[PDB]
Image (cartoon, rainbow, N blue to C red):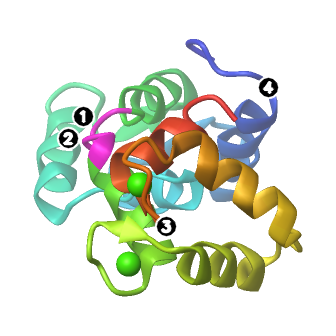
Amino acid sequence: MSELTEEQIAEFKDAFVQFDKEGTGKIATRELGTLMRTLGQNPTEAELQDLIAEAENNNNGQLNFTEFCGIMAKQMRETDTEEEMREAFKIFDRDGDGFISPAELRFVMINLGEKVTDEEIDEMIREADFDGDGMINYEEFVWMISQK
Ligand SMILES: [Ca+2]
Ligand SMILES: [Ca+2]
């Protein structure tokens, strides 16, 4: 609840209880990675053991919803931001040439679940297509989603 909305808050909140349900809102750090994953951020084996032994050095071994909520919050940046971004851009491209052509953009955004019309497609492309290419570049695409 550092600076979240409420929906996400209700999320790890619901995940937290469903893991405890014993009259003590404190889950074992050894099972912390599970929640952060169920949330959106996937922790690495290494970072897990460090924060785990960490709590065991004072918090006995289990963590409270406060410290956790504080953690999921700080985890909203360990994704290297652009790293996860480039990952998605690649998904639409399909090839990985650095630019998503109409066929690549529509085919992926439509196959996932968004039934977009060609007209809307030409709109997004043209707006970000600064290089004036028949394709969107990571820079152009990322820009578009950074507002729209
Ligand atoms: Ca491509
Ligand atoms: Ca372009």
Name the foreground residue: 67 vs 84: 84
In the image, the segment drawn in magenta is 77-82
What is the secondary structure assignment of the residue under circle 3? loop
Cβ(mark 3) to ligand 2 < 8 Å? Answer: yes
36 in magenta: no
Question: Where does the image place residue 63, in percent across and percent down from the top left?
Answer: 42, 35
The residue lying at 82 percent from left, 76 percent from top is 113
Tell me if residue 108 comes above or below residue 58 in the rendering: below
Cβ(mark 2) to ligand 1 < 8 Å? Answer: no
Mark 2, Cα crowd under 10 Å, few <14 / some 14-19 / many 20+, is some
Mark nearer the viewer, 2 or 1: 2
Query: Mark 3 to mark 4: distance in Å?
Result: 41 Å
Disc 2 designates what residue? 51
Query: Mark 4 to mark 2: distance in Å?
Result: 26 Å
First along the sequence among labels 4 and 2? 4
Q: Amino acid at mark 4?
A: Glu
First along the sequence among labels 1 and 3? 1
Q: Which mark is residue 6?
A: 4
Question: Where does the image place residue 51, in percent across and percent down from the top left?
Answer: 20, 41
Mark nearer the viewer, 3 or 2: 3
Q: Would you say 14 lies left or right of 49 here?
A: right
Cβ(mark 1) to ligand 1 < 8 Å? Answer: no
Disc 3 designates what residue? 134
Q: Which mark is residue 55?
A: 1
Q: Amino acid at mark 1?
A: Ala
Q: Residue reaching furthest top?
A: 3
Numbered circles on residues, count: 4
Q: Would you say 78 lies left or right of 62 here?
A: left
